[PDB]
Image (cartoon, rainbow over all chains, first blue to last red; front, side):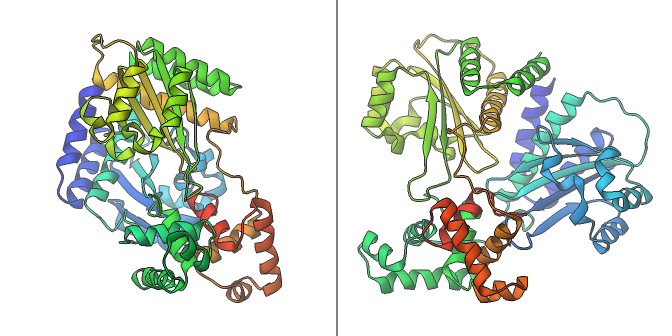
Length: 238
Length: 238
């Protein structure tokens, strides 16, 4: 019965104290579903210009190196949300048509069958969970069951990794005060320092001080990078 | 069996052609679960300073007016994601401790029991689906079943409303070109016009033209409101 699985899995992921426990449980789960490999890959919303990509996987280490060397990330259909239905994507041959070097290379390292599930996280990072397999051997699993289990799996592992503050999920930290974020919102709303000073009954200098303070913390050139970063990662709102 | 419910519901929401069909189906679903009322409320990520809140509900119309008049939105615990587990929130008395005028007033208009489910949408809007009920009469439903059904319901109705472009879900539109968004990313990354001109091999004037163009479209005072808006709603990335 799906329901008790769900409940068991919710608690198990609740209790965990390390990243290594999370990864180890994903691996276990992949095996219950007769997959050999898992990959947990997270695309950050920032930097806007080259988004951070962090992963943990037990793929053959040679495959990780080769995949990076050829920069397959750019063409990986399995990491493009546009290809998904219901947050689910079953690998097959057509999927790879726009990426034939990847397909070949993946098979050459023994990734024959696969599947991925994605989720956007509360911080706007996209998390992808892939399972793949050595054998082309048919393993009948109910489509609906795999889907729902992976749904839970990708979410729970990633929420745990967040609770644990792991480097794979965390966006740049913006430890900002009530007043700083308030200034930041009016900035994102297109208000000038003068205008903010008016709105908040504090001097233009103080507004500017707060601005430079936020920039020091996050090491940003100007207010606009700060506001964008807060806006993209959810840190800007109330 | 949950699985065929799911599959029936996926297709039904797929096929819909109007908002009014979506709302009517939610109402139906609420009734199958012996609730009288539904509410579909969506908190937008923008304006940053007073986020848009749009809803469709069949609550008693007098309750909608009263709720607004007393500005209960500000204190509504049922619309605050911090209160949720697994995107689910069962109404009860403790929940309302920080909001006792709301609790009384809600009961006085006959909202006795209730439940809400939320979801962050691909555009970063938060969608909430509430069911409530007239009677305090005990209706045994498996916690896990309600949860999963509402999960599907809140997501599907809101995705349909998006496919349909309904005013309740849509963020301000930013019909921008490849080049405009490219300029926008470097802006959000804190780059100056001069620097962008360098990076893109085009003149400072042209960069500025693009900037003013984006501002005209969206009626924004400066580049920084534009970039923030694109960053918050997902429109800025690749």
